[PDB]
Image (tube, helix red, strand yellow):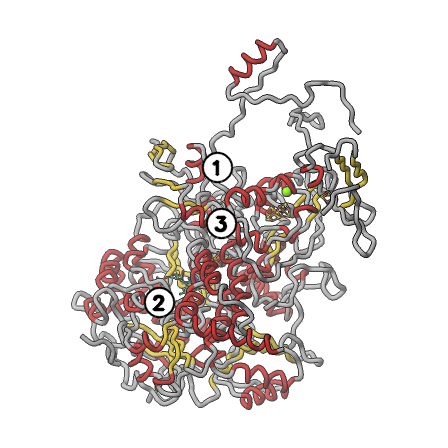
Amino acid sequence: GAGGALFVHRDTPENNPDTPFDFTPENYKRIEAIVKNYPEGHKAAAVLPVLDLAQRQNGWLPISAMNKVAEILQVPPMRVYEVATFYTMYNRKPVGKYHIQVCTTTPCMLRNSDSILEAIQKKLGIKVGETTPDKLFTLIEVECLGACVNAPMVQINDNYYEDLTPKDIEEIIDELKAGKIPKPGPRSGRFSCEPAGGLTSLTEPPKGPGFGVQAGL
Amino acid sequence: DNSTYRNLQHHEYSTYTFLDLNVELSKFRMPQPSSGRQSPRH
Amino acid sequence: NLIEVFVDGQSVMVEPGTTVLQACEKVGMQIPRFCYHERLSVAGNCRMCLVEIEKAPKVVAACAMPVMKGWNILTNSEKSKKAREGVMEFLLANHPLDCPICDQGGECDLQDQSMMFGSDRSRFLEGKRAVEDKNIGPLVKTIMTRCIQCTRCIRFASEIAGVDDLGTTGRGNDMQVGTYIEKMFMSELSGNIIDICPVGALTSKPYAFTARPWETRKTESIDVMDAVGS
Amino acid sequence: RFRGEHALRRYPSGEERCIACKLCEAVCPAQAITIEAEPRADGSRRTTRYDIDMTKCIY
Amino acid sequence: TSFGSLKDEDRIFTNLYGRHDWRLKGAQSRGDWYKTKEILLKGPDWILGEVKTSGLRGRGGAGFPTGLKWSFMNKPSDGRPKYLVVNADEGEPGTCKDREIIRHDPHKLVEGCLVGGRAMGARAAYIYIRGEFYNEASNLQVAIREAYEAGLIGKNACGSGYDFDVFVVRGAGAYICGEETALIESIEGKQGKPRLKPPFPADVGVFGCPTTVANVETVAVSPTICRRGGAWFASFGRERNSGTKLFNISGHVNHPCTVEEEMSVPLKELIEKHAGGVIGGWDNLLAVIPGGSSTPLIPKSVCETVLMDFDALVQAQTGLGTAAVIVMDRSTDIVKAIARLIEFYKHESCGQCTPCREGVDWMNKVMARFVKGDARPAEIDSLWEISKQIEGHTICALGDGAAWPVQGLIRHFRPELEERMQQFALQHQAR
Amino acid sequence: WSSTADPLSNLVLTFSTKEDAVAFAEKNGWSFDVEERKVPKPKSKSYGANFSWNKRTRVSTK
Ligand SMILES: Cc1cc2nc3c(=O)[nH]c(=O)nc-3n(C[C@H](O)[C@H](O)[C@H](O)COP(=O)(O)O)c2cc1C
Ligand code: SF4
Ligand code: SF4
Ligand code: SF4
Ligand code: SF4
Ligand code: FES
Ligand code: FES
Ligand SMILES: [Mg+2]
């Protein structure tokens, strides 16, 4: 389906090249650490990490932030815009405090991911691409997040909440809005990707160093 | 004793945890190779 | 020294590193192309130049594949014709019906290559894509629904004119070529993007609607606006 | 299907149908059609001259 | 002979499920970081020979001989740096093995990076991890810091005189940047559109230097292979498909999980043993996708007698892929599932080249009409032809991976499509 | 309309060779100016030059 977000920028009072933005000195130290992870003469390779750091600092990516990153890296602002528009993890528009991202691909769709999405929508009273009126939660659909064996799952600010049920996700939303921070991970009693019935492998203590080492070494 | 999930250190990380870790091991790196120019535009 | 390749079984002596398209041009065959320009870099994205090597099970992008020793290039093979028809089908499937109102009109590479290498019928039963037009100055008129994302204007802009204010924003079928901001592409070499744009997306604004290519009489003269003598 | 005197039509809104594409001028066997166009005040692709010579047309 | 029943004494990926310590002390309690100096002193040729004898094939999709790839990388230096690039953009819909390896065996991953870099003559190893895996990336950074402090990586790595660096690059969300050349492009701060071969990455990679892209599981099993033999690794598996493999069983199954087994375990045994079988029983099975979304689907008839192996699944008009087993039982809409996969491919297409761009959007629309029957039976062969036009005419393999599920659906469930179209025609006729 | 008085305004002839055209013009008695054919010079194209390690040919976009 259509994304619903345009890939052109029209100047607004809240988003314009004159919007005040700059990195904190700690973020400048982080940028200095990031830049020298790449060979000399290839400073352009830091565009993605620097843009991610700017988004983490500001909460989203304004055109002023993009221009500041371009000035810092001595790279064309159009290239910075290309990167920011290409990669979907960059917020080119302000979002809520908690960014719920429900994975709705086939491995998660086979389990009741639609139930999770409906429970989230009814708990907050917002649609699948809107933000709560108190600017607290934003809800979107996303593709596979790498936790297929723990379907259904959502991501809320780089934390995975897996093996969800409508009651569990409603509890997570209530805990988030109260002020607490829920523990990421499966909610069905599992600790990780192990089968729920019980450990069908790795049930014996691991072998020590040099268990089956070759005779040569 | 393999009944306790020992990967619990990740319920503490913050917004800048990854970048702070990257800063910490900056001193452990080695000098980067040089292309001979400041930028491809140079 | 020169290596020996074959084009439809005809022996050609080409320098190492020469592309399949250049070998075919040397033998006298102009491989159809949209994104390839000899003065620009090699992009290899439109996929219109795919040709078949005699024993290779896979077609190769003739504009980017260097030739090897003893390569027989099948320019007019069934696989090459099917590949060209498929690429043209995709291009015209998403292309809009603007030919009578489009200045490119009778001098369009998409039209000519469609008539020489593509099919004559449409299987596209869905709706088409519409793209918001941009504004990049009083010289170039942009109707971006007609763009085929061949990235000629971007490559020309950067490499030749030293101005990197053009590029692609977004990804997928929603990828758009432009500036992403209200910035005019003002430079002393900005009409060549009008010239090299294979479609009517980039057209001359002063020349808009005035004439059609078959009517114009061409007189070969020189330039006096500067001392270059173009 | 009878072919008689020529005419230029309009859309029901009153706007002229012709878009100055010169296909009729190109295909006219007798070269009896002359067309000159330019952008209109509202930017439409509309003709400023559309002449047909009825002593040259073969109908 | 029979395959499967892998023993915990032979499973390479210990500490899976995160039931043991993942730190340096925990890894050293297992066999990790043992005689790494001896391996490095054995050197590049010996490591490459050991890998070739083990016969390890590519663990991140298209299975190529890793020994052959690293031998390609083993050319003499010509004044340019050398890079091993470890792919951890696990965007494949069905895969969690790389995430588990990173989160629970980061020191195994780091030691594998070091061994691969020594075999390739590489100065640096860039582990490109997807941005969603923030906690996994942080754990990887912690393990890298521990290794640097212990001296296992850095100048004079493991006391062998070989200087080697390990960096972690957090990408953004791009299943296309998952691809090797697109990953290389993304590292350089560009959009992340795949390159054209030639030049191959072994000749011109990231920054233009010789760089070789390897999967997380491949590099993670490399050092265990080096410490052990490789006759043993070749013994585990079929003749031309050797080793152990991580399978992610998910979907309509009782106990979805990630497990490690032999490289030729039959699919039915794997499902019935490590996942509790299909929810409604094996008689309720409808289809299985054995290698993630890219690989086509196989019905219950093929799944009854098939081995989870590269060649075995290739003979089944499918592929092993990334060993992601998605199970769909009889109570599912297979057409809607394949439509969702095609929509995923449409969303994740980089859009560089016309066949995949336009054709994948077109197939998304066609399948969206198919799932409600709003079509005609003549359009199924048209969709097949469109998929064939897409396949093999694209820059990267995402175009091929976006047409194989369509081809599998058309090949195994054409009667369902025709029945749904007839139902829609009947419903429209009534009104 | 655009009138004219030159009979040879629309007269364009096609010749396979410069020598043939020159001979025709000479035997018909008109003056003639000959311009040599301009063929593009062969150019070295390389896709891998877009990713050069130390040269300016590296492209900033694709
Ligand atoms: C996590 C991951 C994601 C991948 N995603 C893609 C993809 O989207 N498209 C593709 O054509 N190949 C993809 N590949 C395969 C790569 O082209 C390449 O084969 C792999 O990164 C290295 O091969 P290996 O298995 O020998 O290590 C992916 C590989 C990995 C490890
Ligand atoms: S660019 Fe070519 S195909 Fe497109 S509307 Fe213009 S003349 Fe027609
Ligand atoms: S605007 Fe024209 S030159 Fe530029 S990418 Fe589109 S078709 Fe090519
Ligand atoms: S120029 Fe002629 S053919 Fe074209 S729209 Fe006008 S009347 Fe019709
Ligand atoms: S096949 Fe698709 S994803 Fe791959 S290069 Fe082409 S447009 Fe990009
Ligand atoms: S399909 Fe949802 S995490 Fe993979
Ligand atoms: S001309 Fe070769 S792919 Fe475009
Ligand atoms: Mg043009």
* Residue E421 in the image: above or below residue E114: below
For mark 1, name the chain: C
The answer, for residue E26, to whether it is visible in the render is: no
* Residue E373 in the image: above or below residue E77: below
Separation of marks 2 and 3 at Cα, in angstroms: 28 Å
Residues marked 2 and 3 touching at CB (< 8 Å): no
Residue in the image at 42% along x and 86% along y? A191
Separation of marks 1 and 2 at Cα, in angstroms: 39 Å
Residue in the image at 67% along x and 59% along y? A8
Q: Secondary structure at mark 3?
A: helix
**The image quarter in which residue D26 lies:** top right
Q: Secondary structure at mark 2?
A: loop
**Residue located beneath label 3 in the image:** C85
**Residue located beneath label 1 in the image:** C30
2 vs 3, front mark? 3
**The image quarter in which residue A44 lies:** bottom right
Residue E336 position in % (x across, y down): 50, 74
Residue at far front of view? D2
